[PDB]
Image (tube, coloured by chain):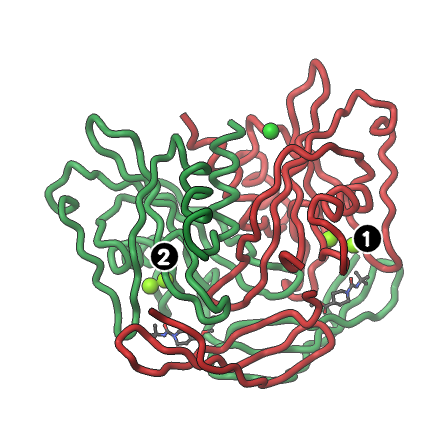
Chain colours: A red, B green
Amino acid sequence: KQYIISEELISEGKWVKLEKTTYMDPTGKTRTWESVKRTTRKQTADGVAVIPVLQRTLHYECIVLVKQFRPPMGGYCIEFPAGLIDDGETPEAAALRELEEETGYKGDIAECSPAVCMDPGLSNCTIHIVTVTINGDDAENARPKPKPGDGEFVEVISLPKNDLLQRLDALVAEEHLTVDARVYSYALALKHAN
Amino acid sequence: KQYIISEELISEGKWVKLEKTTYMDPTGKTRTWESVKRTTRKEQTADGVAVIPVLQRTLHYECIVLVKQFRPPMGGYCIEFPAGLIDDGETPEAAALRELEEETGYKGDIAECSPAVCMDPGLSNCTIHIVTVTINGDDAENARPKPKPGDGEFVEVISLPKNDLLQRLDALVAEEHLTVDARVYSYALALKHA
Ligand SMILES: COC(=O)C1CCN(C(=O)NC(C)(C)C)CC1
Ligand SMILES: COC(=O)C1CCN(C(=O)NC(C)(C)C)CC1
Ligand SMILES: [Cl-]
Ligand SMILES: [Mg+2]
Ligand SMILES: [Mg+2]
Ligand SMILES: [Mg+2]
Ligand SMILES: [Mg+2]
C-alpha cells in the first residue's frame, strides 16, 4: 500500500549520501523523508557482523567483541566484529575474513541471517549477522594474529556469554565506552531467555 | 589515544545532516571520516528509545510485541521493536512507555533501561536507550489494545512467542518482502543460543 515515488539527491560524499525520499502514505497523501545511504553497495547487504562464540574446554563460552574509536561517535565503541562485504564476496566469506582481520581468530560458520536493517528510520543500511563458532583449543587460535589494515587499530575483548549483559554494563560505567545496540540486544536476550 | 579534531558541516536537512569529521589516529596522523547525525538531538542522553515489550499472560507463553511499518529509507516494510525519538525534557523510560502505547495500544511497566547504545557507529552518532517493559496482558487496560498513531503514521502490531521468535521471524521473511531489524534479529538469535 505504501511505496516510494522518487528519490532526490541532496548531497553525495565519497562514502555516504543524503537523499530526500518522496513516498505515498496509505491515505493516498504524498510525503517526504530524509534518507541516508552508503555509496559502496554493489551485494545482499552493505556489511556483515559476526557473533563469534569462543569455545574452549573447561572455560566459560565467550563472545568475542571489538573496541575501536568511531569518528561519528566521537569515542570508543564495543561492537561485534564487522565490516563491509567486498564486491563479489559471499556474506559467509566476508564474516570469516573480517573476524580474522579484526581478532586473529579462525572460525567456523554456524548460521547466517537474511539481510537485516541497521537503522531503518534513517538509512537503507543492511547487514547479515553471521554466527561463527571458534575452536579456541586449536593451534591456529592459540596466539590469534590480527591483520589490521593501514590505520584501523582494533582491540579485542572476550566476555563470558553466560554473564554478558552484566559485563557490558560494567564496561560502560567504568570505561565510558558506548556499547553497540546489536550487542546489547543479544546480551539482553541471553538474560531474558527461558 | 584517538580523538576528534574538527567537525565540518557538509549538508544539513530538516532532520539529518552530513559532516566531514577530522580525527587523530593512534600513530599521530590526522584522518577524515564522513559522519551522519540527526538535527533533533538536544540534551537527551540519546536520540531515541527502542522498547523490548514482553507480553505476559496467565496460561500463555510470553510474547515479544513487534511493529511493522513502511520505512521510506528502506523502500519497504520492516519489523522492529516499538521505537521513537525522545521528546525534549522527556525521560527515556517515559518515552518508551509512551511510544509503546502509541504504536501498540499496550500499557507497559518498566523493567530495565540500558545506557545509551549506538545504532551504526561506523556511519552515524545515533544512539538509543533499549527499555525492557513487561506488559500485564491480564489487566483489562491491555485486553483490546488500540494503537494511537500520530498523523500519517501507520503501524501494524505483531506479537510472537519468545520461545519461538527466530523461527517465527524467518517464517514471516519467507512469506513477504519485509526486512527484520538487526536488533530484533540479534535478540531472537540470543534466545536461540541461550
Ligand atoms: C529522518 O527523519 C525524517 O525524514 C522525518 C520525516 C517526518 N517524520 C515522521 O514521523 N513522519 C510522519 C509524521 C508523517 C509519520 C519524522 C522523521
Ligand atoms: C562512512 O565511512 C567513512 O567515512 C569511511 C572513511 C575511511 N574508511 C576506513 O576504513 N578508514 C581506516 C582504514 C583509516 C579505518 C572507511 C569508512
Ligand atoms: Cl551458538
Ligand atoms: Mg570493522
Ligand atoms: Mg576491515
Ligand atoms: Mg516509531
Ligand atoms: Mg512512534
Mark 1: is the Cβ under 8 angstroms from ligand 2?
Answer: yes
Q: Say which mark, if any, is on residue B68.
A: 2
Which chain letter matches label 1?
Answer: A
Residue A24: give x, y in percent of width and height: 36, 78
Q: Residue furthest top?
A: A58
In this view, A124 is above or below B112:
below
Residue B119: give x, y in percent of width and height: 55, 57
In this view, A164 is above or below B177:
above
Q: Are marks 2 and 1 in contact (CB under 8 Å)?
A: no
Determine which quarter of the picture holds residue A143. top right
Q: Residue furthest front?
A: B175
Which chain letter matches label 2?
Answer: B
> Which residue is the site of mark 1?
A153
Direction from residue A66 to residue A104 in the image, left or right: right
Tell me whether marks 2 and 1 sit on the same chain: no
- Which residue is depicted at the point 45% across and 53% down? B129
Q: Amino acid at mark 1?
A: Phe
Direction from residue B132 to residue B128 in the image, left or right: right
Q: Quadrant of ligand 6?
A: bottom left
In this view, B84 is above or below B79:
below
In this view of the protein, which residue sits in the foreground, A172 or A139?
Answer: A139
Direction from residue A89 to residue B56 in the image, left or right: left
In this view of the protein, which residue sits in the foreground, A175 or A144?
Answer: A144
